[PDB]
Amino acid sequence: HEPMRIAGRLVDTDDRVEVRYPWNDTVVGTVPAGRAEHAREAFAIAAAYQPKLTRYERQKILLATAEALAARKEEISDVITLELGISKADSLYEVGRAFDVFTLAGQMCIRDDGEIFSCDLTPHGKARKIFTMREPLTAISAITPFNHPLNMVAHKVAPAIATNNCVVVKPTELTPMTALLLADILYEAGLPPEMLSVVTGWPADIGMEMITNPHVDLVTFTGSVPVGKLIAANAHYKRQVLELGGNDPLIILNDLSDDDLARAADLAVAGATKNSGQRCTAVKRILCQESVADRFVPLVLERAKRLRFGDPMDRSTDLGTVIHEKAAALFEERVMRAAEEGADILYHPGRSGALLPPIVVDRVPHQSDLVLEETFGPIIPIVRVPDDDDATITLSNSTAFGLSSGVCTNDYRRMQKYIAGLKVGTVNIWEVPGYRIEMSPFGGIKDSGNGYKEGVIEAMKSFTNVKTFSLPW
Amino acid sequence: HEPMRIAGRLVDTDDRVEVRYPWNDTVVGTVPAGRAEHAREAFAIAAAYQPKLTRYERQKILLATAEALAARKEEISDVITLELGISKADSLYEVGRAFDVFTLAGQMCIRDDGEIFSCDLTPHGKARKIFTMREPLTAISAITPFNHPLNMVAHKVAPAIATNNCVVVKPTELTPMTALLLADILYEAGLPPEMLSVVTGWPADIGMEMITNPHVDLVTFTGSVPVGKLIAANAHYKRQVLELGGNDPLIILNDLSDDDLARAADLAVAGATKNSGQRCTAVKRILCQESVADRFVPLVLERAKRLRFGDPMDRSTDLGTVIHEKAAALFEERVMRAAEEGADILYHPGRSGALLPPIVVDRVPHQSDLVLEETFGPIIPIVRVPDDDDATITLSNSTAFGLSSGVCTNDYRRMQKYIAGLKVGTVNIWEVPGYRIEMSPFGGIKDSGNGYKEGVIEAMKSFTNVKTFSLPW
């Protein structure tokens, strides 16, 4: 049972939201059914507090947070696993990503990207210099999905701290406990409490306040397209950074040797199944060029079968559950429709509740629901595509999304072609689409986002206003 | 009579919009009453056309356009003065600004701001490099106001061309002819016609298509606050850069010598009257610290009285008309109401239609409509403020606007204090709020805009998507 964290205080309500363990559906915790007044209260506090931390002080807090995450990693990943259902292997990995987020944010504090312009440049010139600097906003509203109950919150909060902002976070009601814990850790690491609140509740009573509150200068959101559209509809004049789904391909080109085909197969399986397939950058489509398909698919099947799937608290488990059973059943259903339609199910040892095997499907129709819907699970779907790059690129670009991509080839000419021709925010050569460092620019185009980059560095810039000043020179 | 320019094609309608010279309300031209279908065609052409121009070729076009603007400055300035009514002195200066816009955009074509990241940085590190690249959007929608019929269009179009974008401009129906001429100049300079259309019409016919067309990746708008907020609400799901009004102060600090008070007075009069005061960044509030005001105000009055206001085609005219009679009358009434509220009118030769003299009012109450709200005219209003910087800064920050500012002082400590404390996008020491180079970051906060910077460099960046790619290393 965990109250909201509002600027360092615990705030509770009568009604409550139960949080269930997807493995066995038992209640693992409860959080308040917060309402519009609770967000309003947090934003009032954020707006009134003017952080004065030095860069050094911000770095200290962020690095202390990093070391706290490292020291408490077993405790933290337990909380993540118990509400999300991913394996401890995946939970622990997520703690390691959050460790990178805070470490990199702390280290980026020493950097001032201010610029200087000379003004004697044209006939309208003057003997003068212009200098630039950055200032924080009034308040930031952060809304996060169930995907990475820790890292998603880390990415929105660490850069706000690094830039002297005050942030209010509303994590999903499905996985709020990890966020409330991160708040505790931040407070203990020395964060001035007014700089962070974590509120909880049903979307129908508190979500609107997160979007419309008058003190909010910026809304940063990660989640689904429909909800993204609700945000943009209601957050009229406010700055927004929206990261909406992906539908990312791993593309296997026909120049690969058998040995490389095996390495690509490792990529395909990891990419399709890491975090139980629940990543905006998960491999959702393996586009295998026809002429290597017969050699490639078996290698994939063999790797998928080595995957241990079951009790997420078991330290041996590779693959835990998805977010709930309703999601698990739906994905399996899409796998069945695809088979109706021509696909060959090569491995499906059967579903139990929210536990999904790393199902292997070959000859997946590119237009099947399995691929075109967001099948946010550990399905390993192989689409056979033409031994023609123009056709492959066209197919790859044919969804409403454009987030990331991975391409396996040794032909530079082809590499260039895909890098240039794929309509996405990121093209990874010889890596899964989800590969990035926590501080490089991250974001997509089309339905995947509203056109702004995140990641630690770009987030820090987005969370500030540039102010210029000029002096006689 | 000027047709629209749709990708190089002259396109007419039966209905017309009359363009009138504010000096004598006579018709100086006519443009089509364009409809949704015209904008829709323009956008379809924009989206279908993939510019292949090298950086060299873009630079060539941009620099040839600059040369043409300089060669034709008098001709272009004539068109500006005939539709806006600002003096030839002011319109010639505007052509000079557009000259800088095109020159600097052409010269920025050589710059590749791509970044490189090493990936071996944390326990999650890989032997890999990430590289960064920029790509253009599908189509850009640009909506411009009456106050710089040439330069506002130049600022939206030069960076689009510089980035291989395709832009559709809808200039205000009050001053559309300057925009149509710039288009002709661009096509002649070698711009592929598909990269630029200029459409015209009443907002009720064509305005919605500008902000709602499916090919539009970005709306860049400069105009009034109410229209801006209406655009923000109807352009829901699109990227927007909105640059709105200002209410910018010129602050006179009590450390100044009498010699310096005279230099400050020169800035006060120029900044409040240049372009007939029709600038987002015009001096609209002269905040004079009480203990120098008795010495400062006579110096302002003396300078105001020297200004020649009248026929804008007369080359001896300093100050032309404002945009129309309705505007001028509104501004005068605010002056009169300020006086019934305690203000002292020191100079008011009388208004003739759209021609307003450079009215000087002292002891203006900071709450009067004259200064609390944006007065887009050549008024010279002195607000006496305490000899207390904290109080002065609070007063300065107390409007709904936050764009630019000027501060006259020689005390570094105080200079620093204002630079840090004014809630604005730009602080100019010893210059008018309006001073900038055409390529420095420009943009305000609060009601002055939605929080994104423009100017040539920042516009170039906003007009692209950043793609990253990563390679084994």
Image (cartoon, coloured by chain):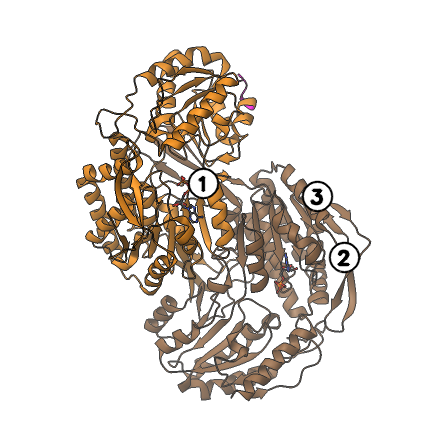
Chain colours: A orange, B brown
- Element class at badge 1: loop
Residue A413 magenta: no
Q: Residue at x 28, y 36 (%)?
A: A21
**Quadrant assignment, res B426:** bottom left
Give SS at disc 2.
strand
Circle 2: residue type: Val
Instruction: State the residue lying farthest toward the left.
Output: A71
Residue B70 to residue A174: above or below:
below
Q: Which residue is mark 2?
A: B31
Q: Mark 3 to mark 1: distance in Å?
A: 32 Å
| Residue at horizontal 41 percent and vertical 56 percent from the top | A209
Name the quarter where the C terminus of chain A is drawn: bottom left
Camera sees residue B355: yes
Give the residue type that dot 3 points to: Glu
- Span highlighted in magenta in the image: A385-390
Residue B137 location in percent, x, y?
Answer: 56, 42
Circle 1 chain? A
Q: Which of the two discs, 3 and 2, labels the residue nearer the N terminus? A: 2
For mark 1, what is the residue?
A: A224
- As for residue A388 lying within the magenta part, the answer is yes
What is the chain letter for disc 3?
Answer: B
Tell me the residue that label 3 is attached to. Answer: B41
Mark closer to the observer (3, 2): 3
On screen, residue B394 versus residue A124, left or right, reads left
Side of B160 relative to A306 (left or right): right
Of marks 1 and 2, the one in the foreground: 1
Label 3: how many residues lie within 10 Å, few (<14), some (14-19) or many (20+)?
A: few
Amino acid type at image mark 1: Ser
